[PDB]
Amino acid sequence: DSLSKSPENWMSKLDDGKHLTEINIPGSHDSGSFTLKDPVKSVWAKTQDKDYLTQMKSGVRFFDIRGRASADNMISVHHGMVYLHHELGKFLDDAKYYLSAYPNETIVMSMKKDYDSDSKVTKTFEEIFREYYYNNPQYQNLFYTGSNANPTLKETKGKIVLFNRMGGTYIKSGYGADTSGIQWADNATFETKINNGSLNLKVQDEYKDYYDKKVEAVKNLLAKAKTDSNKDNVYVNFLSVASGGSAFNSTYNYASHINPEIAKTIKANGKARTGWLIVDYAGYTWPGYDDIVSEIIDSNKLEH
Ligand SMILES: O[C@H]1[C@H](O)[C@@H](O)[C@H](O)[C@@H](O)[C@H]1O
């Protein structure tokens, strides 16, 4: 009866009546850094080792896309300064390709300008994205354009939904899609209203935390999500941290220690509300250890 035995289609099995906030959804942090292959330059920069398409087969439905405008018509996928060797449009095609395959899955694409734009560039990153990406003919059916604020799965089945960190946007469909974007606190657990007071955003993004204070920070959010069945609260709980949490040698190596541990909690809680977990090294499982993504998936309640 376990849903994650087949990660490619896990959503297609939920109740399309559910709001997407009410859906426990695994995500990858810094989703497109999988292209890094210099082991050295990789110690903190690399956060994933699969590609989008596998992340997807693997069960990942929240992607943390970091972008930089390198052209008025182009958004580069970056990790700060570090160009990650593809274009925004690399992600969108693979995703378009993928929903196209598993049409009853939905993806939440977060889009945050991680770096200043190149000198040629003139249009703002939001401008750049509203114009040449969201409002583009090629991606026309893919982006949820829906009127709703608490979008249902039924509504967004087959659509890339926006979790927008671009700031104020002239886009009206997705999460915090409105003129005042989403205020995000630097390095903190914090709460805000988005999409014009329709939804509350409760985030744990304490990315600077030392390793034990990180872990306590995710558990804290997870203990909030668990006992909150309000549709109008969205939870995004970042399991990723800087510097290995000051406890480890590499983001990979840090990853190896948080995920399994967080996985144990989630599993302890059984079928409860957990919100959206953003993990480094999504879909990587160490022999013996619980898998955070799988547990995320199996924490959902599906059929009575
Ligand atoms: O380095 C951090 C980390 O990538 C977080 O996941 C992101 O939310 C922050 O914006 C960023 O400053």
Image (tube, rainbow, N blue to C red):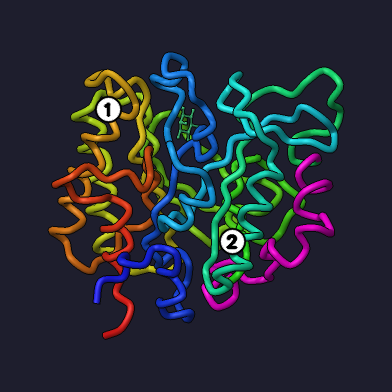
Eyeballing the image, is 31 above or below 105?
A: above
Give the residue at mark 2.
98
Q: Is residue 196 visible?
A: no
User: At 80% across and 39% down in the image, what residue appears?
Assistant: 128
Eyeballing the image, is 181 above or below 25?
A: above
Q: What is the span of residues highlighted in magenta in the rendered image? A: 128-156
Residue type, mark 1 in image: Asn
Residue 274, magenta (yes or no): no
User: At 61% across and 38% down in the image, what residue appears?
Assistant: 112
Where residue 86 appears, as percent x and y from the top left, is: 66, 34
Along the line of sight, the residue nearer the viewer: 180 or 221: 221
N-term mark: 2 or 1 = 2
Give the residue at mark 1.
253
Separation (CA) of disc 2 from disc 1? 30 Å
Is residue 15 toward the left or the right of residue 222 in the image? Answer: right
Which numbered tag is attached to residue 229?
none
